[PDB]
Image (spheres, coloured by chain):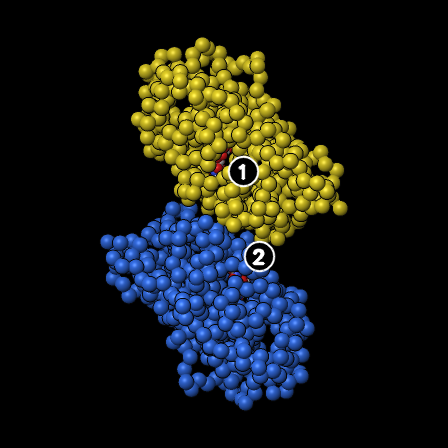
Chain colours: A yellow, B blue
Amino acid sequence: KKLKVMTVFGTRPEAIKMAPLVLELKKYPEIDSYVTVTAQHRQMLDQVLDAFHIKPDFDLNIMKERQTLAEITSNALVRLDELFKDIKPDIVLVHGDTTTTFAGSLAAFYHQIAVGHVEAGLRTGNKYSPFPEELNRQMTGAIADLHFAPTGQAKDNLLKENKKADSIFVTGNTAIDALNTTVRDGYSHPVLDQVGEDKMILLTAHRRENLGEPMENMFKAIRRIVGEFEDVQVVYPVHLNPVVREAAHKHFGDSDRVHLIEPLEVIDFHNFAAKSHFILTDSGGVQEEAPSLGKPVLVLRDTTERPEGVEAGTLKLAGTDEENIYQLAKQLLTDPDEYKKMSQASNPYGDGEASRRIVEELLFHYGYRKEQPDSF
Amino acid sequence: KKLKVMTVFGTRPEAIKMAPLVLELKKYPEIDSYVTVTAQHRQMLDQVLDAFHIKPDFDLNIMKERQTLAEITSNALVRLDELFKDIKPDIVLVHGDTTTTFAGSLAAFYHQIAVGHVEAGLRTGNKYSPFPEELNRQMTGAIADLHFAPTGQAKDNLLKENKKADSIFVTGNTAIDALNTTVRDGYSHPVLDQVGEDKMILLTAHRRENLGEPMENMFKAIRRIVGEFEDVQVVYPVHLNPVVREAAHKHFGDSDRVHLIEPLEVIDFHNFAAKSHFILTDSGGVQEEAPSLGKPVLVLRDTTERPEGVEAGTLKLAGTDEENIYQLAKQLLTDPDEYKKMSQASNPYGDGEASRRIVEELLFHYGYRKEQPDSFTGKLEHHH
Ligand SMILES: CC(=O)N[C@H]1[C@@H](OP(=O)(O)OP(=O)(O)OC[C@H]2O[C@@H](n3ccc(=O)[nH]c3=O)[C@H](O)[C@@H]2O)O[C@H](CO)[C@@H](O)[C@@H]1O
Ligand SMILES: CC(=O)N[C@H]1[C@@H](OP(=O)(O)OP(=O)(O)OC[C@H]2O[C@@H](n3ccc(=O)[nH]c3=O)[C@H](O)[C@@H]2O)O[C@H](CO)[C@@H](O)[C@@H]1O
Ligand SMILES: O=c1ccn([C@@H]2O[C@H](COP(=O)(O)OP(=O)(O)O)[C@@H](O)[C@H]2O)c(=O)[nH]1
Ligand SMILES: O=c1ccn([C@@H]2O[C@H](COP(=O)(O)OP(=O)(O)O)[C@@H](O)[C@H]2O)c(=O)[nH]1
């Protein structure tokens, strides 16, 4: 009989990383696959689904404006529970570390449905950084039957938590599957036109634990850089969270050389990253994409769960102190040795074959294939 | 300033095990303590609160008839979330492995409130046995800042999961704090009067994974034993779950020698256990109580997370197969050597001072005491 697989996800980053897997799953005659979105994000999720031309089988439309963690958890849980009364897949695949990831896993567990965790095992060891992502991924790890770890270090993290080695596979990150298709040699954009010959710093900031004072500190450091370096401009595709938007407007409204724009489609964003001089970000996904692009990243966090990019020299933790961020950005602008150190391209997160590996592992595990795939 | 401590629980077993801790907390002028119940159980919770004379500060009244896991989780989370908007304790203490335990921990975490886990670290390694308790305690363990493990092996379970040693304390189980006060010399009850001279088997059965076929298999075996042995009577205080009640009525409804009764108050239940010939149960708490009483227990499960009781000879895993349960119960009724092997009293789960250790650990952690209390000492450490 055909293996019944359901992907469950709800946000921009999950959708970008899950879309290559959703498309891979469809290529296999022995799999009957379903796509379920919680729509924890609405506009930002639809931007991705539309770009990949993916239409979900089920769309739970849960997003509320300025929603709380309790609200997302309850809404996702209740709606998925209702879904699972009628449709019973053999396995539910969740992604990464959102509240949708955890609620999806929990709803599946409550119906005794098996769970596979895509992007399993990332850790900072700090329950409040990132908040609540660190616990979302740890609690999802308690539920998951199969763990698709992007890297060996992620697998080691799960081993240290007493997970069975034979339930964890090192696949690479599906983000690289997508990234390997988007960059364009001849790329053009109206915003890049007005940047012109100036150095471009690409900025995103949205971590929950960074809202308020930490983000004010980041933005003050950025204002100081722009004021001091005349040949520098910032492009900031601003997250739809109104708390972020308030902070962005407060600091960068009336700035000629900081461009506040709507979130970019992923092909556009990847191409902006490729064109950037360097990146300031607190994004998870951007940290995994940057090494492939050989693009220096100052990570505006006190922690990271991407140590592989740090080892490659691409990623440097800058924290959230104003002066520290200023000094690190100034260094990248004025020290060619430091810039060179941070701008060597490598592929520590994937080779573009992660989706294939995940599906082939599923097929092996359930007895459809006699052989296991290669590891990343 | 006073340390603000809130206990959060909602079911019969949590209330029994948390009651001694609630009362212990009230003793210390250093602590401002609050009691919050979800009332995941209504009647069965109220029975415990009334017995211990505990009046909750907050009662969320969540119980619905035939409620699902998703329902309990959502209702508890939403109501606790609302509570924490208004009241911010320094630490929330949750108990054990119920959906209330997990939802309480999660709600506290969402408000960045510290969590202490009473009865931390119990494991079967099987996510469907017990269901959902194994995962409830595992996920609670991910959230908890402090882990109050009843025994050394529970601490070892947490260490194996990469929990830091300095965050785990071995306290004994608070169940023993309660048990040490309840058994009295000349206990009597109208139901025991009916039993008279006969051997009494005390039965409870309610595990979620046992509902339906497994429980019917248990009950078929038990009905056979009652039929075959005329001097045996069963006392069964039946859980309020309608699903359990249907099965109890189906298999025992016509038997004069199976007493189907309402859930007993804890004082009465403990005294019935003390007077029983042996116990048939799938209860967690009864497994911890029985060694103290030297009472053989056939555990009606395919797993247990009380291995200390198994090693003591008190607990024997019987599974849920009809014939196996019948054979093992028949053995206890007919084999004096086997009965003797299972009826040696010991105290592997506590010495009655668990609640005090928990409170003193809290006071040390937060700087109110210069000294840390000694851990509960087990098995091997006595003797070696
Ligand atoms: C706990 C959790 O799961 N957080 C994830 C969520 O954080 P994020 O900060 O996006 O949190 P939410 O998904 O709750 O969205 C926050 C708020 O932003 C607004 N909003 C968001 C999306 C949208 O399409 N339209 C819109 O209006 C809404 O007011 C919403 O309530 O998404 C991020 C991706 O960007 C992930 O990195 C985070 O791990
Ligand atoms: C997942 C979870 O947390 N399960 C716990 C719960 O299981 P338990 O089997 O009691 O599950 P519930 O707490 O959901 O109660 C089930 C149903 O029983 C009925 N009911 C229950 C209590 C009551 O006072 N009145 C009443 O009418 C209701 O119809 C209720 O919906 O309590 C048991 C103690 O007995 C614990 O061992 C279990 O760990
Ligand atoms: O304007 C943007 C900003 C980011 N991204 C992509 O979104 C993903 C990261 O999502 P986000 O930073 O929202 O969440 P996180 O990764 O931190 O969970 C990465 O693939 C980015 O390339 C995008 O397509 N457009
Ligand atoms: O009729 C009864 C049955 C049990 N108990 C007590 O209830 C606790 C265990 O609760 P339960 O079996 O409902 O749940 P579990 O321990 O399996 O979570 C133990 O302290 C028992 O002594 C009780 O007081 N009256």
Q: Amino acid at mark 1?
A: Gly
As measured in the structure, the alpha-carbon distance from the residue carrying label 1 to the one carrying label 2 is: 26 Å
Taking the image as shown, residue A64 lies to the left or right of residue B374, namely: right
Vertical relation: B302 (above or below) B272: above
Taking the image as shown, residue A295 lies to the left or right of residue A146, namely: left
Vertical relation: B198 (above or below) A259: below
Residue at point 43% right, 61% down?
A: B152
Viewer-proximal residue, B141 or B382? B382
Disc 1 Cβ-to-ligand 3 distance below 8 Å:
no
Estimate the x, y position of residue A236 in percent, counting from the top left.
Answer: 44, 23
Q: Check residue B126 in the rendering and tell me which mark sits there, or answer none.
A: 2
Residue B204 seen in the figure: no
Taking the image as shown, residue A61 lies to the left or right of residue B267, namely: right
Q: Residue furthest bottom?
A: B197
Vertical relation: B173 (above or below) A72: below
Q: Residue furthest top?
A: A197
Q: Secondary structure at mark 1?
A: helix
Q: Nearer the viewer, mark 1 or mark 2?
A: 1
> Badge 1 is on which residue?
A152
Taking the image as shown, residue A110 lies to the left or right of residue A255, namely: right
Estimate the x, y position of residue B364 in percent, counting from the top left.
Answer: 29, 57
Residue A84 seen in the figure: yes
Q: Quadrant of the C terminus of chain A?
A: top right
Estimate the x, y position of residue B348 in percent, counting from the top left.
Answer: 44, 69
Residue at point 59% right, 24% down?
A: A180
Q: Is the residue at mark 1 from the same chain as the one at mark 2?
A: no
Q: Secondary structure at mark 2?
A: loop
Residue at point 32% right, 20% down?
A: A224
Residue at point 46% right, 45% down?
A: A135
> Disc 2: which chain?
B
Q: Amino acid at mark 2?
A: Asn
